[PDB]
Length: 178
Length: 178
Ligand SMILES: C=CCc1ccc(O)c(-c2ccc(O)c(CC=C)c2)c1
Ligand SMILES: C=CCc1ccc(O)c(-c2ccc(O)c(CC=C)c2)c1
Ligand SMILES: [Ca+2]
Ligand SMILES: [Ca+2]
Ligand SMILES: [Cl-]
Image (cartoon, rainbow over all chains, first blue to last red; front, side, top):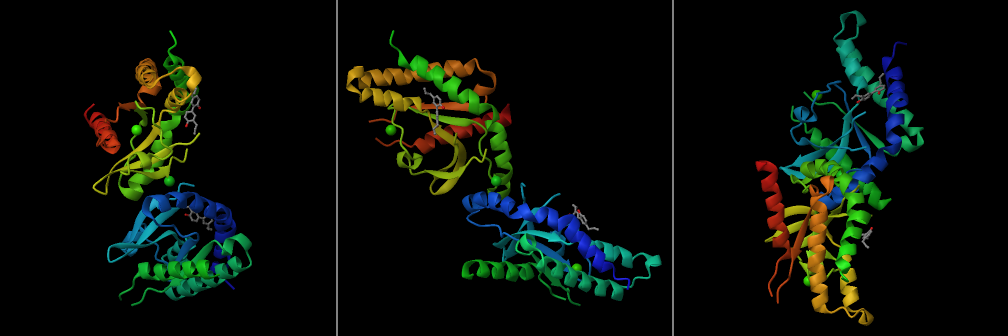
């Protein structure tokens, strides 16, 4: 009954994730030869998808957290590698991306004829997370190479960099134990 | 009258330099995007060809000078990027290569039926330098993208790294002034 998130999630997977994920690991593997050689680091293998529940998608990641600095472009329509800073030290490296459909939810909430409120936007943002999560679960070489980071920035200290970092560190713990 | 260097130089240019040089700059340009991004450095654009007059070609560059450390493989039969060290600091970066025909001159000097002495080898090594130099001079997109480094290690402190470094620094002086 009027749930826009359902089609937004399906569309985001069918029209985008399913197309770009399969080779993303190859792309990152090809790249990681040089990062290991050049900077004695490795870029995580998964695509990290930022799902802020305020549907707030900035144009630069650095505007949302200065500890997230653009690093490089995955050479491989366009994917970017970011470094995560702690105390000015590089703590992690990451192909990182806002889920675009959340801008549609924000735009709908500023569009008066939709009758879509801020409370409606937040419920749709959660449902979009739940739905995309279910879709990836039933997908074979999609769930394995990307992970979803959903968070409400609070009402107000919040480190998006630390929230990505606990995930990056978790992913690595899984690679080496299992 | 029995000058082997003449054919060795022609063959080294016709069969190898002429084939791999034309794109080498593209290869290095493509690569230099990431070195600038990753390590705030740039890999010199020319191919540097080591021409030791003792025809002594080691299997590792580092065995000939520990201040020349392998860095990376030009991604692009096989070309390698080296870093040059000064006091443990990276001072330069460089696609660096021994001229292979000099191994033939060395092997000939250890082959008894050739009647080729160490004095013969050194004259042929010099003539090979002179001849390759003349060939590159009359070649358009060959001379511009490689440079020849000829040297006699003395009889005995000698820094091959410093000898490459003065050249790298000279090449850069030319890029920015002219
Ligand atoms: C209904 C919209 C979902 C949808 C469908 C197809 C797409 O390519 C993208 C998309 C997602 C992220 C992107 O970054 C881009 C390209 C922008 C630079 C497109 C979304
Ligand atoms: C007569 C010999 C000159 C000559 C002719 C064709 C070649 O490909 C090479 C050559 C030079 C440097 C190289 O590194 C290699 C491949 C070895 C890894 C071949 C020399
Ligand atoms: Ca926000
Ligand atoms: Ca030597
Ligand atoms: Cl690279």
